[PDB]
Amino acid sequence: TDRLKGKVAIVTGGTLGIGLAIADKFVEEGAKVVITGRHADVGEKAAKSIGGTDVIRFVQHDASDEAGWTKLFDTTEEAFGPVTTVVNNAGIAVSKSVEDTTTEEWRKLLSVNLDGVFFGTRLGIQRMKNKGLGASIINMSSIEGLVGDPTQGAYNASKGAVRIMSKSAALDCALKDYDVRVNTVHPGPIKTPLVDDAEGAEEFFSQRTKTPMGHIGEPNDIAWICVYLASDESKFATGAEFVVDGGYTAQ
Amino acid sequence: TDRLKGKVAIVTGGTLGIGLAIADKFVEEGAKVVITGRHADVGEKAAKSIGGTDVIRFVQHDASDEAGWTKLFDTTEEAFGPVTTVVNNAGIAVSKSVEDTTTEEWRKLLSVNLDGVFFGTRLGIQRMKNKGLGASIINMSSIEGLVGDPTQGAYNASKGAVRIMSKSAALDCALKDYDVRVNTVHPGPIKTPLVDDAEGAEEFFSQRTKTPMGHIGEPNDIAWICVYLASDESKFATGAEFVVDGGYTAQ
Amino acid sequence: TDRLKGKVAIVTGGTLGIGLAIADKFVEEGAKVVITGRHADVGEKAAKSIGGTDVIRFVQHDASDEAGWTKLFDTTEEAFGPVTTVVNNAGIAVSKSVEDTTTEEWRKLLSVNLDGVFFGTRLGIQRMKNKGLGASIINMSSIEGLVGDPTQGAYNASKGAVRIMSKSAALDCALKDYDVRVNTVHPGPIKTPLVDDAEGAEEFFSQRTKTPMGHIGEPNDIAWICVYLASDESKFATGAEFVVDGGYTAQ
Amino acid sequence: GMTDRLKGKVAIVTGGTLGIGLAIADKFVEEGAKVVITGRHADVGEKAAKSIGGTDVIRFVQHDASDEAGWTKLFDTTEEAFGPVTTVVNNAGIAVSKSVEDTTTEEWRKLLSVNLDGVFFGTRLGIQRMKNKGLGASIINMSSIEGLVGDPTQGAYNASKGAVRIMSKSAALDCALKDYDVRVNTVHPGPIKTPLVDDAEGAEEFFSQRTKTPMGHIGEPNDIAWICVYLASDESKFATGAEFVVDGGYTAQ
Ligand SMILES: NC(=O)c1ccc[n+]([C@@H]2O[C@H](COP(=O)([O-])OP(=O)(O)OC[C@H]3O[C@@H](n4cnc5c(N)ncnc54)[C@H](OP(=O)(O)O)[C@@H]3O)[C@@H](O)[C@H]2O)c1
Ligand SMILES: NC(=O)c1ccc[n+]([C@@H]2O[C@H](COP(=O)([O-])OP(=O)(O)OC[C@H]3O[C@@H](n4cnc5c(N)ncnc54)[C@H](OP(=O)(O)O)[C@@H]3O)[C@@H](O)[C@H]2O)c1
Ligand SMILES: NC(=O)c1ccc[n+]([C@@H]2O[C@H](COP(=O)([O-])OP(=O)(O)OC[C@H]3O[C@@H](n4cnc5c(N)ncnc54)[C@H](OP(=O)(O)O)[C@@H]3O)[C@@H](O)[C@H]2O)c1
Ligand SMILES: NC(=O)c1ccc[n+]([C@@H]2O[C@H](COP(=O)([O-])OP(=O)(O)OC[C@H]3O[C@@H](n4cnc5c(N)ncnc54)[C@H](OP(=O)(O)O)[C@@H]3O)[C@@H](O)[C@H]2O)c1
Ligand SMILES: O=C1c2ccccc2C(=O)N1O
Ligand SMILES: O=C1c2ccccc2C(=O)N1O
Ligand SMILES: O=C1c2ccccc2C(=O)N1O
Ligand SMILES: O=C1c2ccccc2C(=O)N1O
Ligand SMILES: [Mg+2]
Ligand SMILES: [Mg+2]
Ligand SMILES: [Mg+2]
């Protein structure tokens, strides 16, 4: 039995890392999937590496581009039918303390990590409510929405915003019987291009004082909890935080 | 396609309500299960409803009886092989505020809800560590381990204890590369005999000021998260809290 | 006897409501205080209502105005000497679900509630670090930085961002021995002009299902926890959340 | 001029003869409260009381917090000395350096009888004795950062402090819904220099590592006393069911 039977998903930033693995396991469990990203070559190769146009397709869309979001839903519904599932995964990092954060860096990171999740959640509610789809919006927070990090100040702001904004949306949808659920996923450190391109990041976060398991995670670790959250298995889960972090926040 | 292929699970209180559904879906995903209960009559047919002696068996056992835990593991192990999965689900309730709680009520509830979880977790670590089994201890807390209830004082105490004790155990297992994960599950109100017997409770907890979804969940809602937590899909999840509560704690 | 002897505090949005009472009790405990606000008429009287130019002054400044923050510190230090204490209290509300929030409303609320706190915290760290001042940055979050509200989506986002960004700042100041602490305050409902102008709000949040105490608080309730956080009494408190909410988030 | 922040209050501080409790007793008296401190060792207890003030403001009572019957005599004794009790600090607690795996059942029951049952006995009796008297009554239950995060080598302690954390919310809610005029809150110290820490070899050094306490040092008993003063005063009349964390940044990372 396919765990995402009948589901049609948008996965922002689905061409690399966590987003790519969410896409991969979404198709594996029966979902039609549109992945987005900014770079077209990367995006088209990523999509075909999972399957053909009958199951998965790439759409060039910056998650911070408000107007492009309506085209994204229209295109996705054209190819596969009504969207049932939105994974707001696109996100960037900035290695600066609050003290050392430039306003340009601040605004740039928030435009993607916060405005883009807002745009996808607001539009996802409008387009998916009251259709009996078992709709599910999965917003990618982080353990950095739960704890602080002295060199990720703007990132911390954005992931904590996503954490609580998601509860507002969850509550509204539940109280209004919209048949739309909203939850946040909080990965610990995961081996991705994001982490690979940060020199010494994996060794640093593999320290026992950081990740008690003594190693960082893999993209599939996050894909599988997103499968649970996209599926009707989680029909009673809303407004909740799902932490897959090697024990990071437990100490 | 069997998400729990090769797993051997103990499920305390697995003859009614949430425990019964956990066993049901554990076997559907390929796991041998031993369920426990104090009443041999109710417990014997409960085992048969899911299947036969090649998948599931009943073992009479009070969760607060420390010596029986050793017999429970021995019994399970020669029946099905080395135990891989422990779901500490057995629990009782008392409808008293802290002020109105008698010491006998206090002690009785904690012997099951706190001592029993301790016995299963402690022995579960001893018997499952260092065997490459992908061991998982799943400790049933509650939303009542996350927020208070004015007339569930003893219950709140037990569920907050389970919440943080599981983190201790998760951290020690991770730091010692024991290959045992420990997580807690936090159901909101769920239609079970425990709830069916408290008169007017389902209606009370279906109010929007309690559960935002306007209804209470079903035992299968808790079964599917335990499936995720018992499987190797969650191998980076330890010391974390998984909340399935219809939005109850999100407001 | 004076619990804030020698302290020099900037209190943004100090002309009404909570900020006014913070300023009041700060001057009462021997702090020198600059309050800010947008309306000069209201602000000059607000300052005069507490004391003369020797203990308190008003500066017209919009917390979203980044360049003005540098002038605001300069003006405060000219008047009273080096700033020891920054209370990022200016904030606004928008009564819209996520689904109904206009992008105009989103950007406007975040410019005050989030950018304003970022500007104040970042400059505060730069201007107060390494000067033996027992410096303290107090960032005004809300219970709405902890739980969601279906009709305050952007507000929830802002208060969640403030909650976790403040931890980042607290950690970096602690690790670098800056002698700057950073904490967040999380009021529940408080009788202020913000609540009074919102028709039916006080009645709604006084419901026992919302505030278990059956009434909302008053500005001095937040003033006194801010005095504690500004004083050297709290020299071991950093990165933490101080909730004064009538029991709102305890259920 | 300023004013005694605990004028008219009457406090019971369990385990108030050493460490955090002693500092809570000391600053409670400084702020105008009348205090009874408890402890198991009368020698330590009687000198503790005398070091803070006379019997007009503070007295010692030998009492084991696990001893339910003694709680009644304790409140009776405090009433006769000072008047109706207004403030209960459930501070007595002990530790056990064992993982969950390595905890003997005897270590388990002993720690919980003090850390959990003792806080239950004091909270329940505090409510019964202080409800409906308009005293501005406040129950302060001593949890820990170890009621918020785990520690691999304090499994029973973690259990006890997580229980205190949530049981206090139950009591806060019932008290508020019933208009008892009794607030209940928990305090969560990070590592604090006390006899409990001093007697654990290498504990202060371990918890001074930046990976544990970002401030690079542990706190002192007055750090906890001053938040308890706030919680006992009518200044916190709108605070109930909440967690007050004074930990040098430990749980912020
Ligand atoms: N890696 C971790 O340790 C970790 C931990 C916790 C949370 N997270 C979160 O999980 C999410 C995935 O992170 P990751 O580690 O997989 O990052 P990654 O390896 O850098 O992948 C980034 C993906 O997002 C796309 N992307 C970047 N900017 C975008 C924009 N403006 N609009 C649309 N798409 C964009 C990228 O494609 P293009 O470059 O072609 O646009 C790429 O497909 C992020 O939200 C991150 O904050 C990551
Ligand atoms: N129902 C809810 O809304 C809800 C919500 C959150 C959390 N929970 C938690 O989830 C767990 C299951 O609750 P439920 O609603 O399924 O309870 P339930 O309907 O009362 O079923 C409890 C099961 O536990 C067994 N049990 C009772 N006392 C026992 C003991 N001393 N030793 C061993 N087994 C015992 C019972 O069998 P016998 O009668 O034969 O002993 C029964 O099989 C509990 O830990 C509860 O605290 C429940
Ligand atoms: N009241 C509650 O129940 C409650 C609960 C939780 C949190 N809070 C938070 O507490 C803080 C104060 O709220 P309140 O209820 O006291 O609000 P209020 O009664 O509306 O007072 C707000 C104060 O901030 C000033 N202000 C508004 N916009 C500003 C800007 N852009 N720059 C500088 N100052 C500005 C106002 O003066 P001008 O209008 O003249 O500028 C006024 O002095 C806010 O951060 C709010 O989010 C309030
Ligand atoms: N120190 C820390 O770093 C830290 C951090 C977080 C929380 N805490 C908590 O803070 C509280 C105080 O700890 P502390 O570090 O100040 O401990 P401490 O220095 O060991 O002092 C403990 C006090 O409690 C008394 N006590 C011990 N067992 C008792 C019992 N059964 N009944 C009554 N009194 C008893 C002791 O007196 P006798 O010796 O006369 O019995 C002593 O007066 C405890 O709840 C602890 O769990 C401590
Ligand atoms: O992007 C990241 C990351 C990179 C490297 C280590 C930890 C983390 C984390 O927690 N998030 O969200
Ligand atoms: O025992 C209970 C209960 C009873 C009635 C409604 C909800 C709940 C819950 O969440 N737990 O744990
Ligand atoms: O501004 C507010 C407010 C107004 C009225 C009721 C509750 C609240 C709250 O929680 N915040 O933050
Ligand atoms: O009792 C203690 C203790 C002792 C030594 C170091 C840390 C801690 C702590 O967090 N609690 O609660
Ligand atoms: Mg902006
Ligand atoms: Mg709540
Ligand atoms: Mg931590």
Image (cartoon, coloured by chain):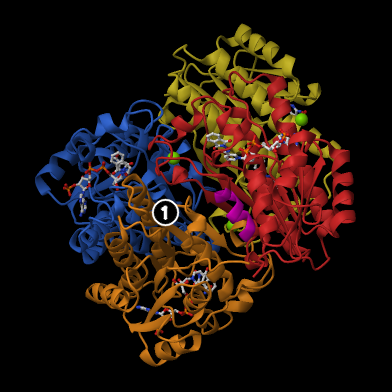
Chain colours: A yellow, B blue, C red, D orange
Whether the residue carrying mark 1 lies under 8 Å from ligand 2 is answered with no
The residue carrying mark 1 is B163
Front one among B130 and D21: D21
Asked whether residue A211 is in view, the answer is: no
State the residue at coordinates (54%, 64%).
D227
Q: Residues within 10 Å of mark 1 (few under 14, many from 20)?
A: many
Q: Amino acid at mark 1?
A: Arg
Location of residue B28 in the rendering, given as x and y in whole percent from the top left corner: 33, 34
Q: Main secondary structure of the magenta part?
A: helix
Location of residue C52 in the rendering, given as x and y in whole percent from the top left corner: 78, 52
- Residue found at the very far left of the displayed protein: B41
Marked residue chain, label 1: B
A51 is within the stretch colored magenta = no
Q: Is residue D97 left or right of residue B211?
A: right
Q: Is residue A115 left or right of residue B87?
A: right
Number of numbered discs = 1
- Residue found at the very far bottom of the displayed protein: D43
C221 is within the stretch colored magenta = yes
Q: Is residue B225 left or right of residue D118?
A: right
Front one among D240 and C164: D240
Q: Determine the image quadrant of residue C155.
A: top right
Check the picture and name the quadrant holding the N terminus of chain B. Answer: top left
Label 1 sits on a secondary structure element that is: helix
- Range of the magenta residues? C220-228
Asked whether residue D232 is in view, the answer is: yes
